[PDB]
Amino acid sequence: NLTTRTQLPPAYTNSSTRGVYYPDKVFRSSVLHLTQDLFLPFFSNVTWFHALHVIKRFDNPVLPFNDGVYFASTEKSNIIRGWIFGTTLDSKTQSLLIVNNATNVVIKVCEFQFCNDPFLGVYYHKNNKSWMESEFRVYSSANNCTFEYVSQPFLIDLEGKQGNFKNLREFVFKNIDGYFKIYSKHTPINLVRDLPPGFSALEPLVDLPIGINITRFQTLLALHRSYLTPGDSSSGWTAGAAAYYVGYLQPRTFLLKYNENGTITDAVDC
Amino acid sequence: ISSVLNDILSRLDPPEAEVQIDRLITGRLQSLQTYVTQQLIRAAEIRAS
Amino acid sequence: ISSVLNDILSRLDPPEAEVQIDRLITGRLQSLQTYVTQQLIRAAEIRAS
Amino acid sequence: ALDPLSETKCTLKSFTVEKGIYQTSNFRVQPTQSIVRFPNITNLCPFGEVFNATRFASVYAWNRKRISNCVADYSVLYNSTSFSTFKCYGVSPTKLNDLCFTNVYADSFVIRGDEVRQIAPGQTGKIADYNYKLPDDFTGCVIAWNSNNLDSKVGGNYNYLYRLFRKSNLKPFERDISTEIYQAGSTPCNGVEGLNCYFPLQSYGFHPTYGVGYQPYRVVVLSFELLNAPATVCGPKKSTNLIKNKCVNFNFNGLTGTGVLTQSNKKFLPFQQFGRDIADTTDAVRDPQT
Amino acid sequence: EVFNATRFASVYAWNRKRISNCVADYSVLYNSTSFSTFKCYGVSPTKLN
Amino acid sequence: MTKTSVDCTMYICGDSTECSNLLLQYGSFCTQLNRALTGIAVEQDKNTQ
Ligand SMILES: *[C@@H]1O[C@H](CO)[C@@H](O[C@@H]2O[C@H](CO)[C@@H](O)[C@H](O)[C@H]2NC(C)=O)[C@H](O)[C@H]1NC(C)=O
Ligand SMILES: *[C@@H]1O[C@H](CO)[C@@H](O)[C@H](O)[C@H]1NC(C)=O
Ligand SMILES: *[C@@H]1O[C@H](CO)[C@@H](O)[C@H](O)[C@H]1NC(C)=O
Ligand SMILES: *[C@@H]1O[C@H](CO)[C@@H](O)[C@H](O)[C@H]1NC(C)=O
Ligand SMILES: *[C@@H]1O[C@H](CO)[C@@H](O)[C@H](O)[C@H]1NC(C)=O
Ligand SMILES: *[C@@H]1O[C@H](CO)[C@@H](O)[C@H](O)[C@H]1NC(C)=O
Ligand SMILES: *[C@@H]1O[C@H](CO)[C@@H](O)[C@H](O)[C@H]1NC(C)=O
Ligand SMILES: *[C@@H]1O[C@H](CO)[C@@H](O)[C@H](O)[C@H]1NC(C)=O
Ligand SMILES: *[C@@H]1O[C@H](CO)[C@@H](O)[C@H](O)[C@H]1NC(C)=O
Ligand SMILES: *[C@@H]1O[C@H](CO)[C@@H](O)[C@H](O)[C@H]1NC(C)=O
Ligand SMILES: *[C@@H]1O[C@H](CO)[C@@H](O)[C@H](O)[C@H]1NC(C)=O
Ligand SMILES: *[C@@H]1O[C@H](CO)[C@@H](O)[C@H](O)[C@H]1NC(C)=O
C-alpha cells in the first residue's frame, strides 16, 4: 500500500552497559547483589533502523521475537507510536496491539486482520497552521476481543521538526506464564546519531494478563504529509527524523550495586 | 522455602513449618561448627608462635 | 533414590526432583568440607616439620 | 529464670558451681502489647458475582477476572454453597484469616466430573494438555463443586465445548481459541474436512440422568502472591493504634514479628512496601494507614 | 484388547498379560475412555512420553 | 588473638518462641561449642603472661 522505497543495506552497532531493570520490588540500600536472569549481554550486536527523507526511508519490517526484546527510540518528534505482537499476524490467531493516537494510548487483544503495511498519518495545512491526524490504517476488522484498555484523553504536539533528537526512550518486553511484562524509561538527550553509551535503570511499568503465543512483532509509525503530489501510495510523505534500535535478551548472571538511596547504579556481566 | 523465619511462621501452620525450621537449624549449626573448628586451628598456630 | 543426576532428571519433573538434588548437594558439600579440614591439619604438621 | 546463679546452674547441668566468671546468655526483653495495622478497606468482596453467577465459560475459553478493594470474609458462603474439592498450595488454610493478598486473580470454567483431578500441578491428560495448564510453582487455591441442577438439560446441553486435538501441549496460563481443521493422516486438509481431517472442538453431552463421572462441575482457581507488592485485598481483622519506642508484637499486612518501632529517614519508591537488611531480614516497612 | 475387553477376570484369579513391541501412544484413548483414578508411583506422568 | 563468644539461640532462632523450643533436642551441642571457645580465650591471657 506504499511505494517509493529507495533501498540500501542495513546498519549495525553494539550496545553499551545498558538494559538493566529492577528484578523485584524490595527496597535495598548499599548492597552488592548477585542475580541470574534474562538480560541483555554487554557489547551485543544491535540493528539500526532509520526514518527520514532527504531517499524515502520508512523501515517498518517484521522481526522475530524470542526470549523478550529490548527497544530503544531516539527522536525529536513523535513518530514511533506503538507495536503489534502476534504469531501469524492474521485473522486465524490472536494478536496484541499497543498504540498511541495523539489523544489516548490503547491496548487491545483481538483477532486482527492486519494490513500489509499499517501506519498513522498527520496532515499539515496552509495559512491556518494545524495538524489533526488525518490518517489511520492499521487493520481491517477485529471480531473476538478478550482484553481492552483505553487511557484518559490528552493531547500532544505533532510537528516539532527542528534541531536534532532531544528525546530517548527505553523499553523492555518479556512474555512469561501468560504475563506480558513491560519496563520503561525516559531520558533527555542531545545527539545526532549512534545511540550514546551510558547506564540507566528500567523501573517496572506494567504486567498484562494476555495469555497468548508470541513469535513475531512489527513497529507502528506515523508519517506527516502536506501539499504535495496526490494519490496516497505514491503521494509523498515527509517523515522527518527518527531512529529505533532492537536487541535480543539471553539468560546471564549479573552483579548489581544498590546505592544509599535504593537506586541501582552499576552492574557487572560475569 | 525461605531464609526468614517470620515468613515461614506467617504462611504455614506449625506441623508444616517444622520441616523448614529443622532444615535452617541444621544449616546454621553446621556453620557455627565450621567457624569453631577454624578458630581452633588458628589458635594452635598462634600458640606455637 | 539414586546416585546419578541424569536418572533423577529423566524420571521426575522438577518439583519432585529438587529434593533429591538437595540431598545430594548437602552430602557432597559435607564430603568437600571434611577433605579441606584434613588437608588443613596435615598442612599444620608439615609446617612444624 | 529466678536468679543469675540459678541460670548458671541450669546452663552447667549440675547443682554445684565452682568459682569462675561463667558467662550467661544475654539481656532479654519481653513485649507488652500486640498491635495490628491493616489498610482502610470497607466493602465486602464480590463473592456472589463470582461464585453465584448465572453462567460460566467454556473450558477452552476459560474466564479470568481481577479482584481488588475487598474484605475476604469467606464465612458468608457457609450457608449458600457446598464445595466438593478445596485445596490450597502455597499457604495453610488456617492462616487465610491473617494475611493480605496483592495480585488476586480468579479463573472460572466448567468441566466433567471425572476431570477435576487434572486441575493440579504436574498432571497430564486431555484437559491438562490441550485446554488448561497450571505452572509448577503455583501459589493459590482450587475450588470445585457439582452443578448438575444448573448446567444440565433434559434434551442435553450443548453449549460447553472442549478441544480434542492439538499439535503440541499448552504452556501454563495460555489460551487458544483457534478453530482450524486438524490433519491426522498425511493428505493435506486444504480447507474442508475429509477422511483424516477433524474439527478440533466437541461439545460435552450433559444429561440429568448420567453417572456421577459424567455430570458437570464448576471450577474456580484463585491465584495470588503474598508478601511483596503492597496488597489490596485483606482479611477480617481489626486494626489498633500504633505503638512506638517499645518492644511489642506487630502484624503489618500479614507480616508478624516482635521488636521496637522508630521513625526512619528512608524514602520508598511508589511500588515498594518492604525493605530488608544484608542478611535477608526485614528492617523497614511502610504503614498502610498514614 | 486390554482396556476395551468384553470380559474381565475375578479379583482372586486376576489376569496377567505381557506387552512387547509397541509405540505406546496413549493419546488415542481420549475420545473413548474416561478414567476415574490414575496414579503413578515410580515416575512423574509428564515424563511418560 | 581476639577472644570471641557466641550465643546459639540468638544467632539461630533470634527472638522466637516457636523456635528455641526445637533447639532443646540439639541443646547439648551448644554447651560443647562454648567449651571450645572458652578454652581458647583463657589460653590467650596465658600467652601474654
Ligand atoms: C484514539 O483511539 C481511541 C480508541 O477508542 C478513541 O477513543 C474514543 O473514546 C471515546 C471516549 O471514551 C469513545 O466514546 C469513542 O467511542 C472512542 N472511539 C473513537 C474512535 O472515537 C479516540 O477517539 C482516538 N483518538 C483520535 C484522535 O483518533
Ligand atoms: C562499541 O561501539 C563503540 C562506538 O560505536 C566503539 O568505540 C567500540 O570500540 C565498540 N566496541 C566493540 C567491542 O565493538
Ligand atoms: C552483527 O551481525 C552481522 C550479520 O552477520 C555481522 O555482519 C556484523 O559483523 C555483526 N556485528 C557484530 C558487532 O557482531
Ligand atoms: C485548517 O484549514 C483546513 C482547510 O484549509 C481545515 O480542514 C482545518 O480544519 C483547519 N484547522 C483549524 C481550523 O484548526
Ligand atoms: C470468534 O469469532 C467468530 C466469528 O463470528 C465466532 O463465530 C466465534 O464464536 C468467536 N469465538 C469466540 C467468541 O470464542
Ligand atoms: C540521595 O538523594 C539526595 C537528593 O537530595 C542526594 O542529595 C544524595 O546525595 C543521594 N544519596 C546518595 C546518592 O547516596
Ligand atoms: C444466587 O443464585 C440463585 C440461583 O439459585 C438466585 O436465585 C439468587 O438470586 C442469587 N443471589 C445472588 C446474590 O446473586
Ligand atoms: C440459610 O439458608 C437456609 C436455606 O434453607 C435458610 O432457610 C436460612 O434462612 C438461611 N440463613 C441465613 C442466616 O442466611
Ligand atoms: C507458538 O507458535 C509457534 C509458531 O506457530 C508454534 O511453533 C508453537 O508450537 C506455539 N506454541 C504452542 C504452545 O502451541
Ligand atoms: C484510614 O483511617 C483512619 C481512621 O482512624 C484515618 O485516621 C486515616 O486518615 C485513614 N487513612 C487513609 C489513607 O484513608
Ligand atoms: C470397543 O469394543 C466394542 C465392542 O462392541 C466396539 O463396538 C467399540 O467400537 C470398541 N471401541 C474402541 C475404541 O475400539
Ligand atoms: C469422538 O467421539 C464422538 C462421540 O462418540 C464421536 O461423535 C466423534 O465422531 C468421535 N471423533 C472421532 C475423530 O472419532
Image: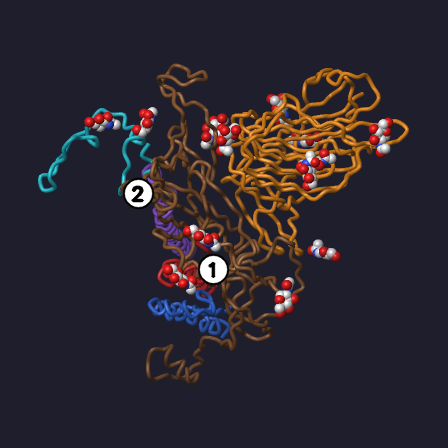
Chain colours: A orange, B red, C purple, D brown, E cyan, F blue
Q: Quadrant of the C terminus of chain D?
A: bottom right
Specify the label residue B7 is tagged with.
1
Residue C24: x and y in percent read 35, 47
Nearer-the-camera pick, A128 or A167: A128
Locate residue D121: give its quadrant.
top left
Can you say whether A194 is above or below C15 in the image?
above
Q: Nearer the viewer, mark 1 or mark 2?
A: 1
Amino acid found under the numbered disc labelled 1: Asp
Amino acid found under the numbered disc labelled 2: Ser
Residue A171: x and y in percent read 65, 38
Can you say whether D116 is above or below D4 in the image?
above
Residue C15: x and y in percent read 38, 45
Please name the residue that numbered disc 2 is placed on.
Answer: C3
Check disc 2 and report its element: helix, strand or loop.
loop
Q: What residue is rendered at 66% in x and 45% in y?
A: A201
Q: Is residue A236 left or right of D184 when viewed as pictured?
A: right
